[PDB]
Amino acid sequence: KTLVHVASVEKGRSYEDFQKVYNAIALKLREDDEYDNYIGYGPVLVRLAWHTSGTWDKHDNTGGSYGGTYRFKKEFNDPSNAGLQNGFKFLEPIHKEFPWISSGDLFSLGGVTAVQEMQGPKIPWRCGRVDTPEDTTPDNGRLPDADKDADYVRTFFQRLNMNDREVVALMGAHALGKTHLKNSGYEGPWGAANNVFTNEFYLNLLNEDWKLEKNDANNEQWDSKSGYMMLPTDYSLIQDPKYLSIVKEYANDQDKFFKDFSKAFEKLLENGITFPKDAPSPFIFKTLEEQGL
Ligand code: HEM
C-alpha cells in the first residue's frame, strides 16, 4: 500500500513565476554572505532540500518532498536536522514575498537555486508539491547515520531507490559547507572550495592523507593535514571496491559528475510525486549571472 501524491501547479503560475522566486533566493544568497564564517547559505540550503526529501520511503510513499512537512515541529526538531533551522529562517522572507508557493516547492527550489548559484550543474525542477497536514509528518529516524560503513550506506539508500552510482554522485554534495560539532558531533570542512560546487570531494578522498582520529565529541572521523575531514560514511566510498571505482570516475571527469549529480538530485527531489501526463515540463532556471543580474 502506497499513498499517491499528484503534483498540482500553484494556480495560474508558470516558469516566469518560479524564476522570480529563484531570483529572490539567489539575490539573498548573495546578500547574506557572512553566514557561517562567510561560507554563505548555499550549503545549508542544499542540505535542507536533501533532508526534506530524504525522509521518503519507496515502500509506502511516506515522507518525501511533497508535503513540505519540515514546517511541523516533529520534523523541524529531528536531531538529524540540527542546523537546518538556519536554512528555514533564510527562506522565511522568501515565503513571505511569494506566499503562493508550496513549502515543498520552496524547500526543493532552495536546493536547486543554491547548487546553480554556486556554479554547479543545472538541475531541472518541477513545481506542484502540495502542503499536507501535520499528521502526515514522518517520524524522526529516516535520515542516515554518519558513523557506519559502506554496507550501511548501500542498504540505506535502497529505501530512496538510489543505486551505487546515484549514491556516490549525491555524496559529492559534501564538497559544500562543513560539519559543525554542536549540530552533528563532527567537525570540519571536506575541502577548500566549500561554497563553489565542484568535484573536490572525490579528489580529496583519493588524494589527501587521511588519519582516523577522535574529535572533541569523542566521535571518530578521518582528518587530513590540510585541515579537511571525511565522515566514516564518506570514507566508506573508498573502502568498498564498487564505490571506489565510481569515486575515481568522478574524480577524473567533472562533466560526468555534474550530469550524474543533476539527475540524481532531481530524482531525490521528485521521489514520491506523480506528475500528470499534462504537467508542465521541468523548468531549467537561469542563474543571476546568466540574466546579468
Ligand atoms: C550517508 C549519507 C549522508 C550522511 C551520513 C550525511 C551526514 C552529514 C553530516 C553529519 C553533516 C554535518 C551537519 C552539521 O554538522 O552541520 C552533513 C552536512 C551536509 N550534507 Fe550530508 N550526509 C549524507 C548525504 C548527503 C547528501 C545526499 C547530500 C545532498 C545531496 C548532503 C548534503 C550535505 C551538505 C551540503 C552539508 C553541509 C551543510 C552545512 O554546511 O551547513 N549530504 N551531512
Image (cartoon, rainbow, N blue to C red):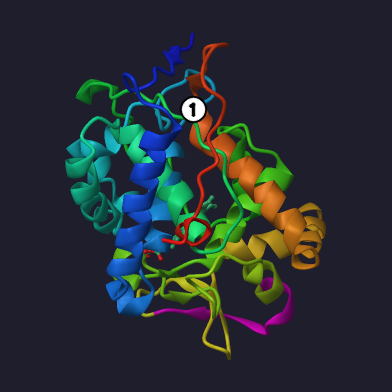
Residue positioned most to the top? 1
Measured as percent of width and height from the top left, residue 275 is found at 52, 17
Q: Is residue 206 magenta?
A: yes
Q: Going by the image, does 66 lie left or right of 268?
A: left
Magenta-colored stretch includes residue 57: no
Residue receiving disc 1: 57
The image position of residue 82, as x and y in percent, is 29, 56
Magenta-drawn segment: 205-215
Q: Quadrant of the C terminus?
A: bottom left
Q: Is residue 189 above or below residue 141?
A: below
- Local secondary structure at mark 1: loop
Whether residue 101 is situated above or below residue 116 in the rendered picture: above
Q: Is mark 1 within 8 Å of ligand 1?
A: no
- Residue toward you, 249 or 157: 249
Residue 221, percent across and down? 52, 73
Q: How many marks?
A: 1
Does the rendering let one see residue 97? Answer: yes
- Category of crowding for the residue at label 1, using alpha-carbon neighbours closer than 10 angstroms: few (below 14), some (14–19), many (at least 20): many
Q: Hey, which residue is sitting farthest front in the picture?
A: 292
Q: Amino acid at mark 1?
A: Asp
